[PDB]
Amino acid sequence: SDGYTIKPNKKVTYSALGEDERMIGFSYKDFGISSSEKITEVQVNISANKNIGKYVGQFGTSTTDSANGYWAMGDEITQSISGNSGTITWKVPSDISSIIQTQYGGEIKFGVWWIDCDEFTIDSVVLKLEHH
Image (cartoon, rainbow, N blue to C red; front, side, top):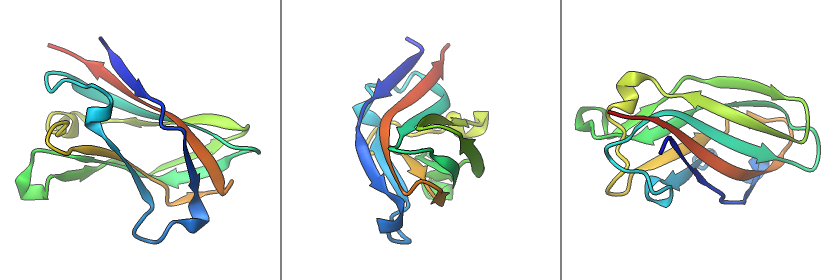
Protein backbone atom coordinates (compact mmCIF):
# COMPACT_ATOMS: atom_id res chain seq x y z
CA SER A 1 0.00 0.00 0.00
CA ASP A 2 0.76 3.76 -0.10
CA GLY A 3 0.04 4.86 3.43
CA TYR A 4 -0.77 3.99 7.05
CA THR A 5 -2.90 5.72 9.64
CA ILE A 6 -3.13 5.59 13.44
CA LYS A 7 -5.92 7.08 15.57
CA PRO A 8 -4.46 7.89 18.95
CA ASN A 9 -7.24 10.27 20.09
CA LYS A 10 -4.59 12.02 22.21
CA LYS A 11 -5.76 15.10 24.07
CA VAL A 12 -3.01 17.70 24.38
CA THR A 13 -2.96 20.82 26.59
CA TYR A 14 -0.12 22.97 25.23
CA SER A 15 0.25 25.16 28.35
CA ALA A 16 0.63 22.04 30.55
CA LEU A 17 3.66 20.75 28.58
CA GLY A 18 7.07 21.35 30.17
CA GLU A 19 9.86 22.87 28.07
CA ASP A 20 11.23 19.38 27.52
CA GLU A 21 7.82 17.81 26.68
CA ARG A 22 6.73 19.79 23.61
CA MET A 23 7.43 16.87 21.21
CA ILE A 24 4.68 14.23 21.15
CA GLY A 25 6.10 10.85 20.12
CA PHE A 26 4.52 7.92 18.24
CA SER A 27 6.20 4.57 17.75
CA TYR A 28 6.61 3.65 14.07
CA LYS A 29 5.67 0.04 14.96
CA ASP A 30 2.13 1.27 15.79
CA PHE A 31 1.54 2.05 12.06
CA GLY A 32 2.56 -1.36 10.73
CA ILE A 33 5.07 0.21 8.29
CA SER A 34 7.62 -2.04 6.55
CA SER A 35 11.32 -1.16 6.43
CA SER A 36 11.15 -1.51 2.58
CA GLU A 37 8.77 1.52 2.36
CA LYS A 38 9.88 5.15 2.02
CA ILE A 39 7.99 7.90 3.84
CA THR A 40 7.31 11.00 1.76
CA GLU A 41 4.86 12.79 4.03
CA VAL A 42 3.58 12.87 7.63
CA GLN A 43 0.14 14.34 8.37
CA VAL A 44 -1.28 15.13 11.78
CA ASN A 45 -5.05 15.69 11.90
CA ILE A 46 -6.20 17.74 14.90
CA SER A 47 -9.45 19.15 16.27
CA ALA A 48 -10.57 21.41 19.09
CA ASN A 49 -13.75 22.75 20.74
CA LYS A 50 -13.13 26.13 19.08
CA ASN A 51 -11.19 27.71 16.19
CA ILE A 52 -7.61 26.44 16.24
CA GLY A 53 -5.78 29.45 14.78
CA LYS A 54 -2.01 29.36 14.41
CA TYR A 55 0.32 26.42 15.00
CA VAL A 56 4.13 26.66 15.01
CA GLY A 57 6.29 23.59 15.31
CA GLN A 58 8.58 21.00 13.79
CA PHE A 59 8.69 17.26 13.24
CA GLY A 60 11.50 14.94 14.21
CA THR A 61 12.28 11.29 13.49
CA SER A 62 14.62 8.50 14.52
CA THR A 63 17.21 7.62 11.86
CA THR A 64 19.93 4.99 11.28
CA ASP A 65 22.64 7.70 11.20
CA SER A 66 24.87 7.28 14.33
CA ALA A 67 27.05 10.26 13.32
CA ASN A 68 24.02 12.53 13.82
CA GLY A 69 22.74 10.84 16.98
CA TYR A 70 20.10 8.72 15.20
CA TRP A 71 17.91 11.83 14.90
CA ALA A 72 16.78 14.37 12.31
CA MET A 73 14.32 17.28 12.35
CA GLY A 74 12.36 18.91 9.55
CA ASP A 75 11.81 22.64 8.88
CA GLU A 76 9.71 24.86 11.09
CA ILE A 77 6.11 25.00 10.03
CA THR A 78 3.72 27.83 10.66
CA GLN A 79 0.11 27.14 9.86
CA SER A 80 -3.24 28.93 10.39
CA ILE A 81 -6.29 26.69 10.77
CA SER A 82 -9.44 28.79 10.54
CA GLY A 83 -11.98 26.26 11.92
CA ASN A 84 -12.31 23.56 14.61
CA SER A 85 -10.25 20.93 12.73
CA GLY A 86 -7.28 20.82 10.38
CA THR A 87 -4.20 19.00 9.11
CA ILE A 88 -0.52 19.74 9.63
CA THR A 89 1.81 18.31 6.98
CA TRP A 90 5.50 17.58 6.88
CA LYS A 91 6.89 16.79 3.41
CA VAL A 92 9.88 14.66 4.32
CA PRO A 93 13.16 15.54 2.51
CA SER A 94 14.64 12.67 0.45
CA ASP A 95 17.84 12.61 2.44
CA ILE A 96 15.97 12.19 5.74
CA SER A 97 13.44 9.72 4.33
CA SER A 98 16.25 7.43 3.13
CA ILE A 99 17.56 7.00 6.71
CA ILE A 100 14.38 6.95 8.84
CA GLN A 101 14.57 4.19 11.38
CA THR A 102 11.12 2.58 11.66
CA GLN A 103 12.43 -0.44 13.59
CA TYR A 104 14.05 -1.09 17.01
CA GLY A 105 12.27 1.71 18.95
CA GLY A 106 12.15 4.32 16.18
CA GLU A 107 9.63 7.13 16.53
CA ILE A 108 8.09 10.03 14.69
CA LYS A 109 7.71 13.09 16.90
CA PHE A 110 5.28 16.00 16.47
CA GLY A 111 6.67 19.22 17.97
CA VAL A 112 4.28 21.93 19.17
CA TRP A 113 6.22 25.16 19.87
CA TRP A 114 3.01 27.25 19.96
CA ILE A 115 -0.69 26.83 19.29
CA ASP A 116 -3.40 29.52 19.69
CA CYS A 117 -6.14 27.12 20.91
CA ASP A 118 -4.57 25.60 24.02
CA GLU A 119 -6.36 22.25 24.13
CA PHE A 120 -6.70 20.10 21.03
CA THR A 121 -6.88 16.43 20.15
CA ILE A 122 -4.63 14.50 17.79
CA ASP A 123 -7.30 12.46 15.94
CA SER A 124 -4.96 10.76 13.49
CA VAL A 125 -1.41 10.59 12.23
CA VAL A 126 -0.90 9.50 8.61
CA LEU A 127 2.27 8.34 6.83
CA LYS A 128 2.32 8.65 3.06
CA LEU A 129 4.70 6.44 1.08
CA GLU A 130 6.41 5.61 -2.17
CA HIS A 131 8.16 2.30 -3.29
CA HIS A 132 10.75 0.40 -5.42
